[PDB]
Amino acid sequence: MDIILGIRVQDSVILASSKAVTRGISVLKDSDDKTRQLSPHTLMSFAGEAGDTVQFAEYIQANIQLYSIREDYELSPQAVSSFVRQELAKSIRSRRPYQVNVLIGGYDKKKNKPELYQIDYLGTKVELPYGAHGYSGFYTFSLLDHHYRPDMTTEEGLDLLKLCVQELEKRMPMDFKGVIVKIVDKDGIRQVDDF
Amino acid sequence: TGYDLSNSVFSPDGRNFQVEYAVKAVENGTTSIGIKCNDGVVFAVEKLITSKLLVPQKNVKIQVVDRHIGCVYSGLIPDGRHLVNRGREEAASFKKLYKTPIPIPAFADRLGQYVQAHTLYNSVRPFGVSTIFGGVDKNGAHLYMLEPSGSYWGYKGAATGKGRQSAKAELEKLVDHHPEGLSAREAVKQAAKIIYLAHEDNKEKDFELEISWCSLSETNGLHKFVKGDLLQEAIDFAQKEIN
Amino acid sequence: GYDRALSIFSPDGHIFQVEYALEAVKRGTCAVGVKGKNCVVLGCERRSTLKLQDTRITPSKVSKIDSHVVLSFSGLNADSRILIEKARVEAQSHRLTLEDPVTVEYLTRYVAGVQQRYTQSGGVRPFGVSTLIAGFDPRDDEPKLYQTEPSGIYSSWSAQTIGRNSKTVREFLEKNYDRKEPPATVEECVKLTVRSLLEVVQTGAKNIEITVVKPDSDIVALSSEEINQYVTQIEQEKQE
Amino acid sequence: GYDRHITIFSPEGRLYQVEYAFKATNQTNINSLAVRGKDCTVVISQKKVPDKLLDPTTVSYIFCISRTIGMVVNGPIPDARNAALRAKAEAAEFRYKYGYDMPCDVLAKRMANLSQIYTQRAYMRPLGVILTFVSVDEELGPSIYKTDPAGYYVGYKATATGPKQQEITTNLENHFKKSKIDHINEESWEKVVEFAITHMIDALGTEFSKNDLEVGVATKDKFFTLSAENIEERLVAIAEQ
Amino acid sequence: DRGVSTFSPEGRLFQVEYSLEAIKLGSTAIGIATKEGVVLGVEKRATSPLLESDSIEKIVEIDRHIGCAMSGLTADARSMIEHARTAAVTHNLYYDEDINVESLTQSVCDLALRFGELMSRPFGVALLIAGHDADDGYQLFHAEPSGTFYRYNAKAIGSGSEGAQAELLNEWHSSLTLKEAELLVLKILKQVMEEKLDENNAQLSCITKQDGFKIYDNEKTAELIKELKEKEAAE
Amino acid sequence: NNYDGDTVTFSPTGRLFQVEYALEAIKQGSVTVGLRSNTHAVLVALKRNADELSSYQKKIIKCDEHMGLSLAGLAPDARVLSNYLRQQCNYSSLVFNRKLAVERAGHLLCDKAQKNTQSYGGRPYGVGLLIIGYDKSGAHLLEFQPSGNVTELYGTAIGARSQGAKTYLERTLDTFIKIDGNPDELIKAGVEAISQSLRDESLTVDNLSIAIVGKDTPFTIYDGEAVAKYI
Amino acid sequence: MTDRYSFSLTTFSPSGKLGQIDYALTAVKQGVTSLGIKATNGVVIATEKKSSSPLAMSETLSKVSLLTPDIGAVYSGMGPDYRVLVDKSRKVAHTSYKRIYGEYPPTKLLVSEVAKIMQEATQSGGVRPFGVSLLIAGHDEFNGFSLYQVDPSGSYFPWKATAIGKGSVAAKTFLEKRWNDELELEDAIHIALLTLKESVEGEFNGDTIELAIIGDENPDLLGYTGIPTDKGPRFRKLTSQEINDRLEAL
Amino acid sequence: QFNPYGDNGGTILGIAGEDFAVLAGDTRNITDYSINSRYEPKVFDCGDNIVMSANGFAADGDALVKRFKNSVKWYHFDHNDKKLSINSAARNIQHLLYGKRFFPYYVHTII
Amino acid sequence: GSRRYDSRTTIFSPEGRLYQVEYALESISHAGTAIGIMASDGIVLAAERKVTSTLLEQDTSTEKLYKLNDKIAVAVAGLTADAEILINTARIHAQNYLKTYNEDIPVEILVRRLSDIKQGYTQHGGLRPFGVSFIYAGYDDRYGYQLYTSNPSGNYTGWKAISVGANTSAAQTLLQMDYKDDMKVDDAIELALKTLSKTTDSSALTYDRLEFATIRKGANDGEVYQKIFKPQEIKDILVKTGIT
Ligand SMILES: [Cl-]
């Protein structure tokens, strides 16, 4: 785990998530996809405690997919984010809390608007134009404060994101083995293969 | 009607027919007695010898609770054992909390409340036994008789089973002829006589006599079975009186 | 907790509560399943003593259990929701642990097991429902059609019907369905299904529902006009 | 007709099991009576020991519930003792929880509430008993409160219970019509006991030896039962007047 | 009504006796034990021609060395099989060995009387349990809803049982080959079945020490059916 | 009649019909015999088959190294009760390093059977048991009835036509009680006893079941060719 | 042992009736008459004190009960059932309202809670319905004065005035002739006493009649001073003497 | 704070031949610097030609041997007096030990 | 034991019907009629109070029409006490959904869950079913205006216009006659009142024997308003359509 970023632009939400899985002094994998598709127009990235992350992600995925089949309908990004927040807000006072931080990028088809939600393991939810979890934010937030505009295109968002990855690759202590980038818009979720 | 099909149901009389039906099971059983004496109590019971193949002295029916109380019963033998098992639990918890061994009146109400509880619900059956029990405590000797309804009283003498009326008549004579009191050793002999006299109401099969006693002077306030010389002496006394 | 053994054996060896649950199925609206060479079609009767209905919002007779499997039924409507819900939950649970959607056989086996459990559990009555479960196994193009019933038995069928007058439509299917040559196309399969319902239904108006399931999660429900074209075409060939 | 077997309503709105429990009340064929003095509350009951083999000292239908509360029962002894043990436990708990002795009327209400539950809940039968609670309450003074299998309860100037209760009731009514007061205007409890026995004799039309009666007396800070000789002393006093 | 665990005046449990009637309505299942193996055969009995007969599963594997056939309310058998499989695998986990056929059968029969007012009623299905172990070799057991199990050299259960059992009484001897047993099950099934016996409405299976429990193909059984018809015509 | 719906109901004459019906299941069971001397205790049991293709239902069960029983009636109920005895014998060994007295074994079975005769929902056990054992007071034989009644005897028999063996043992009492230090003779007496309960059938090699426990003999069961000696 | 009665004892008959509820209402019909009248500035509830014996002290048996300082209750039917309902009603006013909001519940909501308790005795396992109809009078700041009837089924209705029990049919007709929307509390007390005399047979005085009002706040009945916002209970039980005063100008 | 474990010392040794096997152990039992017993055996015949020793904390050692001996007894009861093979015993003992994974038997076991 | 007194509320008849459900429906058929009519710009709920007394407080009264949330209401036919148990459950369920998803609950989801509770009382637990039939009137942004009904069986269906309680057969025939799809709210108000007026068992339909409610988008811009009619407002609407 470690680096997960998110940028909301004019027409889409872009999520970038690091590919490394490190345990001890060994990088066990350099192609890890730290994300789950909750619904056709909703994507969740995650970072935190080993085991907890994927277990929580897949548990949420199962619940949203169950809802979809039951109602023959897709929950709004706002509705999904609130469900996820509550699950984490329950968790934090359990015997063993989920130590997982998530970003939820979705395209609301009723509003025709992209939406990005940042939720930490405590269940602290905020809607943001751009978001980050962990130490990443300490570099990317100030960078985005300067270069981000609300009316940017998906291409402009990807260039803005390249600027973030470059900064992290220059100043971060650990080798996070690049990022997998995914776009969420009116047409659903797709992966950028050459980043 | 149908009032008699379910336990705890009042009939229009105000009766619980299921308890009265349990009393019939008691009347069907063998005779057992209790005699209160100067400083203790004596228990005796009729053991029908169904076959030559029964090992003599080896199907013991009188039961001890704690170390100072004796219990005997007529009717469904397993039901009596259940009641004694509870009695032993009740006595153990009393001694645990209060240190002193359970007094006889205290013990009597423990059994009474437990048997009475089995007349409160349709999901349980009343006890098919009348139980004669007692012993010696700090206030002297006590003898009790407990019935399927949960009813119990203190007794000078007590009898139940198929030969209860014969035994009761014989008990009443002792109470009249001995206003000052009967001795423990005398009461053992009398118990033998009364069981032999009450055996007339069950005389197809011959029987085996079983006696026990608690006495402040003779057994030091503890429950003991009468065996050997004292038993044979009591049997002979009884044999002489029937002829 | 309520404990009463409601489903018990009778002197002749029958469990009447299970058998009476079958009578509830016999009262329910007719449902039919026919599988072709490359598809399965589920047809369902809807009674017309109910005008002023709102068909947008009224519960549909065929339910998606997952994106690749569907379930139709005959009998008590309220009962069927409980089975459908449990099936949908198991569908997601299977994907979670096995990392693969359910086979139609497995999903059927689960639903049948639930039904069986309600025949020897205290305090419960059996489900007044028989189901037709149809679909395609993951990465498989062979059509699957299964039937369950209140007792808990389940089996595979080339074509099958349940509900009221199902014995009449089963008769039709038994002479009109060739095992050696199943309906080669979607059109052929839908037509044979619509034909079989027209033996029992009444008007081919808003009385027949048709749902077509094709391989790789390809499920669509036909509209009134689309079904009405099959009704119109069949009647014109009949006058001969 | 299973509506007569458990405590559910009959078509005419009646509870037959409760009604039949009232008939179980008289199964012992014993009559009880309670009156109030200025300083005391006296309760008396018949004592019938038919069997010669019984230990007469163990035959009792009067119970010492607490130091201040006494209770006489009309009904079979198993149910009577069941009620007594519960009443003792309830009174003991009340004192522990609330820091003062349970009043007679409050214990009566509590036992009446328990009885009510058996009339509403099916698995529990009513107890075939009528419970008369007596005390000298520190707030209300001399008190008589009575409970039945219906769960009904009320305070009394005086009361009677048993097969021949109506005769005793009217006898007492006629005395209080005459005296114009709510109690026996007497200083000592000894004479209130004498009044109680006198008016029971008149109403029942029978004479009593020392072993035909049972007497409980409640005074401030204690309830106690009388011995055979205490009653004999009381019988002699009545005879010599 | 009356209690589920009630005794009749003749000293039998009503519900157990009534479940035995349900089993008599079931489809026939036959088992024969030899020194070369145990054969299990069943009548499928499809209720309608449209029903795909190969989905009728009345012969079932419990472990590699134990197989099972059923007759009666077959839906009731699912949880019995589930328990049997778990018992077998669990014993292998705890003891690093195969579980004895008798011990398996005893475990299944322990479920039987766990009903009353535990499940609400007895099972309405009888089981033929066939297997091999090193101690007692090839074995065949008949497991009833009474909780009782008998070892058999040969046994039939279901609607045609009493007629088939009388036939098995005459035909069985201690020197039967596996092939002889296969033909004998087919022969006796064909006798008691309603519809004409073929590879689609009847199923064979066996358990051998060497190859374990195997359900036969429809092609393999068809040839045994043809071999049987030819041998009966040949005298 | 109206009072046999469950065990919780007494009849007007004070009978428990469900318990009596359970007793009836024992009478239908195959005969089994029990007898003892001062040194050994012996069980003999006639086993029953379904037909000539079936096995013979095992009647004898080992409870401990010094105790065991034979059964007549519902076999699953014997399995439940024997399992309980196995546990009780075992508890006595693990906790007190003490072999369970055959008498206590009887008391425990009585109390277990009794609880099933006083509560709603349950049913009486439908099996009779003959328990033999050798403990600190020598050889023992017990008879268990599902009414709860347990009885210590020199010899006895339960099952169909058990009255024949029970009469024989009653006559033979003085002889077999003094067969001390001779196992084969005590068995011979038991095999002759069970022969008084046979009709149209005789004792064969896969029909007879014998068990013995004693002073220098653990509870062991004999079947098959090991009982050919006694036919 | 244990409550094996986990099933409903009140069930639908083929005709659609719920037998036990009907039979409970029958028990209410047999019960002694009680009534309630709503005035513009108060509410009155009244009933006859049917004495079981003249040796009984009828003061010790209270048919009219305070539930909260502003709510009172009276009944017709089975006394014991009523007594436990009052216990439960007093407790539920605290547990489900006062302990949450720091104030007493409004009349309609307390009534709603009592109705719930009575409904559950109609559906739950192993119980019969309550054999009582209640009349609950009360006041609260935002609804003013109100009067409710609660039946064995659990149903409740608001009333301007009504009667229940023995002679309810005649008493309701009497109240229809006399009730207007301008009645002052004293006028309502007068009409309550008139209506009750019709159904009472024997003695008719302050010792045989039980009557309470919901009216003005009573600072003298509060028991303490110093908090301006606490002004005292609106529930007041009229004394035996206060009833006789009004029976002279009758 | 109460410490539920102790160390009773001693040592054990097992060697296997072609048609035999030995299991040896000293008979000394200790706590700290004191001798509790000079002859307290900790190698036991468990039946079915299986010998066993659980060395370390003797209370746990005795408990385990006791439970395994009891396991052999019930294996006979449940599987028609079948002999418990050494490999089956080993697997059974694993489950006895792992059953207390989060409160272990403090012993080295050899059979 | 207690088996003797068990009615067995959750069993099948030989014909495959649920006795208790059928008998509960028979009970409901005697309750006051309630009508729901769905228009293109709103929904009408109309219900007849059960034979009123002149001394009944009419304004502070609620018997037929209950509010579940700001977007959903129900009309009741059957035992009121039973209905309130279910209404409180439904109210809580709506708030659970709003708390979880931060969106008002879709009407069908609420209807399904309430209907699922009813279903449970017919399959397990040995308890009597709820003697209640609901008409659900509500709005959400998926399907807009919706009418549903549920009954003791736990079965629910959607409607353009529907009646429950007494005289449903006659009421349904009248609604089926005069209802058309392009209908407006004010027309639906008139149809609801006209139908009750013809199916009523009373002599004449008056304001004091009615409860009335509308669910319109007749607030200000793209939002829904629930109007539970006051007594005087029912008096006026009854005059405006010329029934009195
Ligand atoms: Cl209380």
Image (tube, coloured by chain):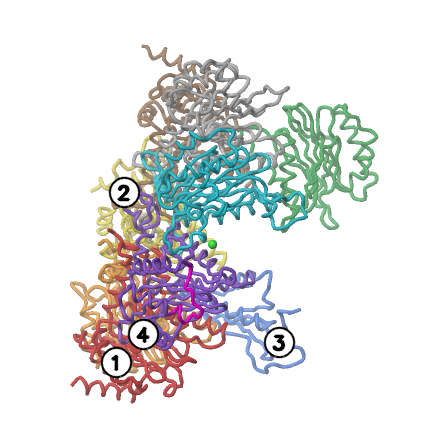
Residue I91 point in image, percent of width and height: 54, 35
Kind of element beneath mark 4: helix
Mark 3 surroundings within 10 Å by alpha-carbon count, few (fewer than 14), some (14 through 19), many (20 or more): some
Queried on whether the Cβ of the residue with tag 4 lies below 8 angstroms from ligand 1, the answer reads no
Say whether marks 1 and 2 touch (CB < 8 Å).
no
Name the chain under label 1.
Answer: B
Residue identified by numbered label 2 = E25
Amino acid marked by disc 4? Ala
Q: Colour of chain F?
A: orange
Q: Which chain is cyan?
A: G
Label 4 belongs to which residue?
Answer: D239
Q: Can you identify the residue that label 3 sits on?
A: H10
Are the numbered discs 1 and 4 placed on the same chain, yes or no? no
Which residue sits at x=25%, y=82%?
B176
Q: Which chain is brown?
A: C
Magenta span contains residue D187: yes
Colour green belongs to chain? A
**Residues drawn in magenta:** D181-193
Q: Secondary structure at mark 2?
A: loop
Q: Residue D45 lies in magenta, yes or no?
A: no
Chain letter, colour purple in render: D
* Residue G13 quadrant: top left
Which dot, 2 or 4, sits closer to the camera?
4
Q: Mark 4 belongs to which subunit?
A: D
Image colour assigned to chain B: red
**Who is closer to the viewer here, F157 or F188?**
F157
User: CA separation, marks 3 and 4?
Assistant: 94 Å
Say which of marks 3 and 4 sits in front: 4
Q: Could you tell me which chain the residue with mark 2 belongs to? A: E
Residue beneath disc 1 = B209
Q: Is residue G139 left or right of residue I203?
A: right
Q: Name the residue: 68% across, 34% down.
A: A104
